[PDB]
Image: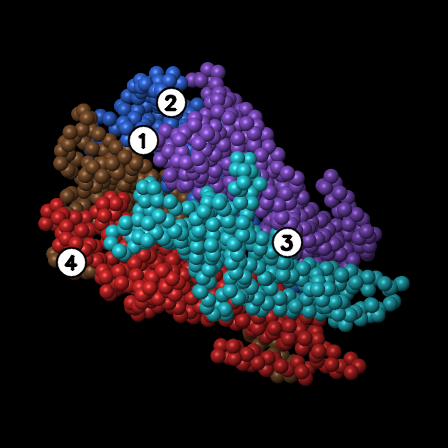
Chain colours: A cyan, B purple, C blue, D brown, E red
Amino acid sequence: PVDVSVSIFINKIYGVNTLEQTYKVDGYIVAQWTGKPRKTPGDKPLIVENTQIERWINNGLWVPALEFINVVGSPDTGNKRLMLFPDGRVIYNARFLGSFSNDMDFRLFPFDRQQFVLELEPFSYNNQQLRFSDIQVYTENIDNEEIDEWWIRGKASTHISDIRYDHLSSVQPNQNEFSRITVRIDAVRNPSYYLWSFILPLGLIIAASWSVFWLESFSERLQTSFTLMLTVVAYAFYTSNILPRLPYTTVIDQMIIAGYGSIFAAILLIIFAHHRQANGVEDDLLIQRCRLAFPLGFLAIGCVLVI
Amino acid sequence: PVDVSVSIFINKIYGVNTLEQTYKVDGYIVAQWTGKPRKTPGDKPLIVENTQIERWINNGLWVPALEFINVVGSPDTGNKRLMLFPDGRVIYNARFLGSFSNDMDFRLFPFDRQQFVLELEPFSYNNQQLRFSDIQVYTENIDNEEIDEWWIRGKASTHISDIRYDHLSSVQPNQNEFSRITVRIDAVRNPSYYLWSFILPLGLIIAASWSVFWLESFSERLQTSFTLMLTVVAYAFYTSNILPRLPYTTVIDQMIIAGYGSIFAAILLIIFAHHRQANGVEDDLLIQRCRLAFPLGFLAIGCVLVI
Amino acid sequence: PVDVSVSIFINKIYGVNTLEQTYKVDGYIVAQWTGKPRKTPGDKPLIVENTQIERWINNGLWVPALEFINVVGSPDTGNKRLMLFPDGRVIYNARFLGSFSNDMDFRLFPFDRQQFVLELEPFSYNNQQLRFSDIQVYTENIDNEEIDEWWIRGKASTHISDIRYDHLSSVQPNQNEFSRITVRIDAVRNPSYYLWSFILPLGLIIAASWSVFWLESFSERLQTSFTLMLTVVAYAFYTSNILPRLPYTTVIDQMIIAGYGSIFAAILLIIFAHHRQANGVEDDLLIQRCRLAFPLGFLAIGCVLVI
Amino acid sequence: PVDVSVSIFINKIYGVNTLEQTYKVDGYIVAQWTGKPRKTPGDKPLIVENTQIERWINNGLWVPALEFINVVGSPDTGNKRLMLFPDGRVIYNARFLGSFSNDMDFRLFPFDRQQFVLELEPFSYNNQQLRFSDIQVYTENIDNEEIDEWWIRGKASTHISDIRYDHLSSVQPNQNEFSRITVRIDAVRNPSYYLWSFILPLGLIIAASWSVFWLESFSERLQTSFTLMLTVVAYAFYTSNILPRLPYTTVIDQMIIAGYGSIFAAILLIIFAHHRQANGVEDDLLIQRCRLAFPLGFLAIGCVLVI
Amino acid sequence: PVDVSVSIFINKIYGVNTLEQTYKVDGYIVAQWTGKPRKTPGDKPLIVENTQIERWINNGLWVPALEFINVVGSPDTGNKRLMLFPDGRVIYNARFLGSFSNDMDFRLFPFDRQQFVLELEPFSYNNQQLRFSDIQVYTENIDNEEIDEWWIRGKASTHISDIRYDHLSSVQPNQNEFSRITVRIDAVRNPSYYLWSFILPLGLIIAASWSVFWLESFSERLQTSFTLMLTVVAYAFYTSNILPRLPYTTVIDQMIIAGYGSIFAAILLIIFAHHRQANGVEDDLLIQRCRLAFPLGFLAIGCVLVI
Ligand code: NA
Ligand code: NA
Ligand code: NA
Ligand code: NA
Ligand code: NA
Ligand code: NA
């Protein structure tokens, strides 16, 4: 076979779509193999720019097609390079930009912990005709973490493994496995903005909903509860426009549902408290002293849902 | 004719547009037929990469154009392969990405049951010059269902049928039918997020609207009803921004309309209850005891609209 | 001249932009003319696939360029076909997708009645060098009307006419008219969702605004009117986000403006009713009995604005 | 030099981005110059379709590149024509679509008065090698003004002028000026929808804010003022979603800010009126009679801000 | 090596994405070097238009590839020029449009101070084979600052420096540094619209929240506080839709959080004031006199958070 050493450069990672489970990675790719010696002009290596590689391909020069497994569509390939040493080795350099898919679980959304995965595999040649010797990833673009959405933790890991296809055994007897390169890039979401702007006003609004039990008029308590329900609906629509469109509930959504249930339970308990009277002589005071038990129950519910 | 065996690979399915009735499917397509024997270099099969297929086409090699019937525009074709065995058989491999249309009914929106349909047909050659022998679809990319919007149920089905065009009989006497391949992929929408975040707060808000009959002041009942109407408008706009823009009402929209009607009926009944007095001496109490009949009537209306 | 018979296929129509007055039409186009006889290989007709038409064009084969007059930019041309009979006739087949402009009036928005117009004209050749014999449009893709936004009524009409350009008389003495094909496709908007979700809650909210006159406290009437005004603002923003961005008011916008005016008139009349007293002894009762005349006046205003 | 007569056709103008200061213009461009005589086949002029112009360019035919100065990126060039008379003159025809930038001031937004400017200049040849003789613009596509966003007033004006570059004097001694064509197209925004749907409900809401002084309870006046403030916030968010994202305030924004200030001043004056009492015996009546001076002051403020 | 003089023209700068940290720059690039003398037709320099440069490249003419380091994908290259003097010097001119990344800190969002950075470096040739002599940037397009989002302050600065790559030492012994050109363009955000439409109504709403302490009824104070909380939620959602989606809080977000905390503290203090009574005989008056200390405390908090 032919040994190919791959170097992958990463510039900057963006375009995370939560519903589509795609993210955009921009950077360079460097591929280097060894071929037959050629007589280049001069002792210096010969270099071929963009839109001149096709002339050498039509001449008969052998270059492989290293596609990305998890990319959708085609990557936006920029400038391409093809530098030919006279002693035999060929270095291929190109710049790409594409949307890459992954599993990308989003439970515990403000405190996410997910990895960006890049997969590389030759589109044409199998293990017996093309191998990957080693890959050194270059995630050198590391800057201050305070103004970035994603916190890159540690250094990216690389692995080389063989992938066997079951459907290639129909026409190919013993050569049906392909060399694949997988690169994992760990990242942690920045939780400062979400914690400061979403979690804390939920706590303040939920405490405001707890505040309704300190009143003395039943009808005015009902109107206060309906105003609190409208406030919770308004904050729910405020969160849902800014939060992404992932197909399952987060901690914020569970907090919103728990607040809805708390308002409904408050309405039911004050209605039951006003109409516990035998003949209208009893006061709604004995069961109305849940002002120091209802927030403790909600805190217990919160501690249950976190764990 | 020429027999062609087609293999269709599916990577991941996304981009469902409810108004446009389109969805995006990414994957590979493999086409294999048999031709005249050729003298390739060596006993190994000859393989042709991307942007070199056109040279063989200009040379005189016969390849067909297998278009997708239901795609809009043109698919984003990635890397293409053309591998030539010396004993005669030709294998064509390509990767595509495009938006495919379907019927895609969206009634009962949180509990959808719809199929993704891929259609394949040669753009040029009819039944007497090109046939499809068989197709084996490979929907092997199956993962955990908990973090996906669509639940792939079962295995995708394939069918080969002939489609006859009426307009081709003007110039073609007896050869006017085309071999078509149709692939059905069943899917079920994930209902957990919608049921937890939309259906339940509608029930809580509708119960809060039922709660207005437990008051004792007519004017305060009117103000409570207007506050409840504003709350229902707020939740309606909260749902309509997050719910898709399908051109007909769902179960959630019917629930919202029923809540609007319930508030209007509550307003009309309390107005009629206050002004049923002959000379202002009667109390609004006899007809106001619909507090345990109005929710039962709404539940009956709901049971009617579900069935 | 050369006679050309055009067949236009329509797949599905979507992408209606109300502000841009554009819509997207996908389908096929078939052009057929007659040329000099040629010696094709065998008695069977010779067929040319995609990206091989240019070789025959460079050889000297005459094909025209049939552009769309009302399209913006360039259509997304898919696979193209070029089939050469040996007795002389040439059949050209292609698939397109583009955004087509029209007048597209949107007054009476929920009950629209507008036509989709496709225009075809040769980009290069005039009447003396190219003619259109006839066109048969194929709008065969007709399905159930219940789940579609647009109701296709009847069958599409076709017309062939000559268009004369005034600016071509500077260099061309007597040949300045071009053969043009115009295809009209009638369509009616689906009014069920709009009528169920927008018109009816406007009626309910306007009746709720009528309900304010049944109170007995002037200050509480003012607060009720301000709450109703906030509700109408909320529903106005609910409609304006979902309704399109056409540059003029619809029936829904006129209803919203009339509701605003009704609330303002209610506020002015109750203010005048409270302060019609000579020395504070009169009751606001005689002029406050417009509870059964104000809705009739609003219904008269509605009947005026519909007609 | 070589004289070139340019004809510019305009189809329809759309895509106005207020923040980006770009607009989309679709139409044709016709360029005509005179060259050496050639022997075309027959006495009829020879015509070259799309994707065959490059063959004549490679042969040695001289065509210039007429770029647009104010376009961003590249225009979406459709079909191109190249018609060669045998007596010498060459006519070049092409269709374009691109986004053109301008100054495009947006102060007095509902009553805008701005011009669309198209600039043309050869990309390669200066005044001594290429000149523009004259341009006749064809804005013939004029229709009814009632259903269009922009009112085209008058006929478009054209001007031919020379533009001198300072940086070209380093290598070019006396030939550093370029012939430029500038076309001005005047347009007026349609004010009917904005005046009916935004300005009038602002007046109604501001009158509703004026209505708070007619009450008799200080606390109820405060609650009414807070409800009016919430209504003004709701209408502000209703306007800001539909109004464009221009980086400075319009008349509507100034009206909204003035309404905010009016509510704040009303709150401050009623607070001062309640607490002007020496020992709680005075009534808030003498300074509370600004009910017929505060709207006059707001009208004076409005008349100041308009002028 | 070969000396290359670069001239960069800037047309207009737009498309600032706060989350993606990208901005769009349109303009020209001019590259000039010196090569071997050639015999052009005539004493005039020979000029090569678009889509004819590739013929000279295939002939053997040496042109470099000057890529942008910080661009994502590929720039939208418009018309390209290649003008060949007969005495030896080559001038290359091209027009580009692309999205360029930067650090682009957004703290103190209404009063931003950030620089637009353009980086240029040859994609292929190192310092020993290609050098940049000097660059003169032309930011001549300066207009009135009143109608622009970004205020260009001063003149753009240019710098030429060498960038050494560590990974190129594996195959290249002593030639591993690349000549890079960096251009800084300073800009200041326009603060007039933000200050007039966001900061001032926050102050008015916060003063309205301060106004709640002037009441005399505890329950009515609670309802006023809940209405103020709903108003603050409404204004928060009004700001968050118009403000960008940067991943950290701005001054406006800190003001909103401080207003939430002020409302919660007001609720807690009035609840504590009503229930400081030993047996219900005390009045909530002594601690309720924080009406002239709570705004001073909030102003102190604001002065702390600004500094
Ligand atoms: Na009240
Ligand atoms: Na709202
Ligand atoms: Na929105
Ligand atoms: Na909204
Ligand atoms: Na309220
Ligand atoms: Na509200």
| Residue A68, percent from left and from top | 48, 49
Between the residue at mark 1 and the residue at mark 3, the CA separation in whole angstroms equals: 55 Å
Between the residue at mark 2 and the residue at mark 1, the CA separation in whole angstroms equals: 14 Å
Same chain, marks 4 and 1?
no
The chain identifier of the residue carrying mark 3 reads: A
Residue mark closest to the camera, 2 vs 3: 2
Q: Determine if residue B12 is in view.
A: yes
Between the residue at mark 4 and the residue at mark 1, the CA separation in whole angstroms equals: 43 Å
Between the residue at mark 2 and the residue at mark 4, the CA separation in whole angstroms equals: 57 Å
**Which residue is denoted by mark 1 in the rendering?**
C55
- Element under disc 3: loop
Q: Crowding at label 4, few (<14), some or many (≥20) Cα neighbours within 10 Å?
A: few
Q: Quadrant of residue E167?
A: bottom left
Residue mark closest to the camera, 4 vs 1: 1
- Element under disc 1: helix
Residue mark closest to the camera, 2 vs 4: 2
**Which residue is denoted by mark 2 in the rendering?**
C46
What residue appears at the point 46 percent right and 66 percent down from the top-left corner?
Answer: A142
Q: Which mark is residue D171?
A: 4
Choose the circle earlier in sequence order: 2 or 1.
2
- Element under disc 2: strand
What amino acid is found at the position of numbered circle 2 in the picture? Leu
* Nearest the eye: E291 or A253: A253
* Nearest the eye: B296 or D222: B296
Q: Which mark is residue A248?
A: 3
Query: In the displayed structure, does residue C261 sit left or right of residue C47?
Result: right
